[PDB]
Image 1 (tube, rainbow over the protein chains, first blue to last red):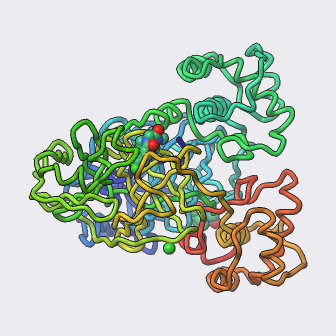
Image 2: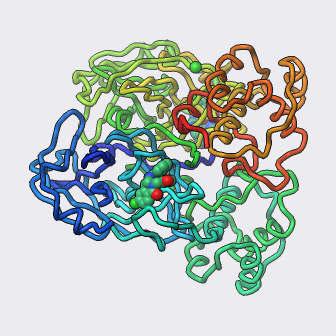
Length: 298
Length: 305
Ligand SMILES: CNC(=O)CN1C[C@@H](C(=O)Nc2cncc3ccccc23)c2cc(Cl)ccc2C1=O
Ligand SMILES: CNC(=O)CN1C[C@@H](C(=O)Nc2cncc3ccccc23)c2cc(Cl)ccc2C1=O
Ligand SMILES: [Cl-]
C-alpha cells in the first residue's frame, strides 16, 4: 500500500556527472564514454563565433577530484560535446530518447558536477517542466530506466519568469518554442494531462479509494467537450487503449472512469481527498501506476 | 525557483542492497563492510508470525541456512547474531562499494529518503517523514522488507530506517539500524494499529517560509499570537504542539524573510480557519508537513524573491 511520487534509482546517472567550466561560467556535464555533453551556453549570442575562438584547454572538466583533459569539441544544436582523453569507466548502458508531453522522468539536480537531489516530474503539455532548480543547475539531466538501460531525455538549460524550467533532449533540440538566450520568453498557457489523471484515479481505486466512483458512463466525444472547458488535454482512443490494463484490473471501464472525472470537474471533491491530495494529480502515467503497483526493479 | 519533494541521490545506498533468503522467505539486506543487516523475521514462516520466539528459531540455524546474493554473486555467511529486531549476518567479503556511513535514530517530524527494493534490487526512491505516531506513509509491496531510509548530508550516508511491516491502514512500521522499532510496534502478526496521527506543525511553518522565499505572501495577516494561544487553536485541528525548540529552529528562516515565528503562527491559525479559497501554496491545496526547517534551507535559495 501507499502511493508516492517515485523516481528511478539515480546511481547509474550519478556516475556520469561532471563539472564544466569555461571562463567565468560553471555548469554540469554528462560524461558518457569519451564525450562530455553540456549546454552550449557554457561558452557565453552567435555560438559558432564564440566557439571558433575557443581551444580545448579553455574548457575545464572535473570528475570528482580528477581533471579530465579535453582533446576535441563540437556543437550539436544547443549541446556542446567535449571529447575527452578518458572513457568513463562508470558509463552505463544508455540511449538518447526524445519524450512527448505527458511523459514523466526522473531528474538528478546537480551543482558543480555534484548531485544534490532526485525528483520525479512530467513534461507539461506547454513543454516546460515544473522543476526545482537554482543557479548552477544547468546541465542537470532527466532520465528513465528500462531494465539496465538509462534513457536520457532531458538536459536543463534555463528558468522562465514564472519559475518553470526549459531544456533540451540530449541531441540539443529544445522541448518547446524556447531559445538559449536571455530574451523575452514565456511559458504558454498550460493544460492538465487527462490520461495521467485517469491513471491516478485507477491507482486510488487499487489502493482502496472509491468514493468518486459512480454508476454512469460517457461517450468519448461528450467527455472531450467537458475536458476542453476545464483546460484538460483531449483524450484520444490511444489513451483509452493504454488505460486498458488498469480498467481490467479494477473492473471500471475507461469511459466509466471518465464519468467520475467529469463529476469531480463539475462539482469538486467536497472536502475530500484522493491519495492524500485535494487536487487532481497529473504527473503519473498509466505505466508509472502499473510499475509502482507491481514492484519493477533495476 | 520551484519546490519539490526531493530525495537524496540513491547511488551510495544502491551499492549496498543485497537479497537475503531463509528457506521460503526472501527479503532485502544492507551490506556494509563484512556485515549484512536485515529484519530478523526472515527466519519466520507466515505461521511463526503470530507469536514467534526468535531466539528459539535462530538457535536451530547454521550459517549455510542463510543465502545472501549481491548482484549475481553469492556471498558466504561465516557468522550470525541478533541485535533487537535486526539479524546481522557476518560475510566473508567486505562490500567494496561501502560508503562513509553512520547509524542514526531519528525523531518524529524528521524526513528521509527511502530506496524501495525487491529481491535485493532497487525499484524506486521517494522522500518521506517519520509521522508523530511513529509510522511512515510509504509505498511498499510484499517483498520490500529490509528496504532502507537514509539521509546524505555531505558525503556520509546516515541510515535511519529499515522496513519491517505494513499495518492494517496501509501505513508502515520499521526500526532503526540497531533493530529498535520506531513506535509501540512489535515484529509479530498480532492486532496492532497506528495511533491517531497529527500534523507536523514545525514542518508546515517551514514550508510557509519556503513559499515566502519563492515569492508568495497571500496568506500572511497583520496579527501575531502567543505560543500558548497558537497551541490551543492548532491542537483543535490535530496539529502537534509547537515547542520553544521549534521556535528556535525556525530562527534562520524568520531572519531570512523578516517574518517573526509567532507572526507566521498567526498566518497558520488563519489558514486553518479559512482554508485556501481556490488558492494554492507551492502548487498544493493542502498544508504540507513533510519538509523540515533543514530541508527548506537545503532546497530554497538564500535570497528571498
Ligand atoms: C531566471 N534566470 C535568469 O534571470 C537569467 N538566466 C540565466 C540562465 C538560467 O535561466 N539559469 C537558471 C536555471 N535554472 C534555475 C535558475 C534559477 C535562478 C537563476 C537562474 C537559473 C539562462 C540560460 C539560458 Cl540558456 C537562457 C536564459 C537564461 C537566463 O535568462
Ligand atoms: C500487510 N501485511 C500482511 O498482510 C502480512 N504481514 C507480512 C509482513 C508484512 O507486513 N509485509 C509487508 C511489508 N510492507 C508492505 C507490505 C504490503 C503488502 C503485504 C505485506 C507487506 C509482516 C511483517 C511483520 Cl514484522 C509483522 C507482520 C507482518 C504481516 O502482517
Ligand atoms: Cl531527528
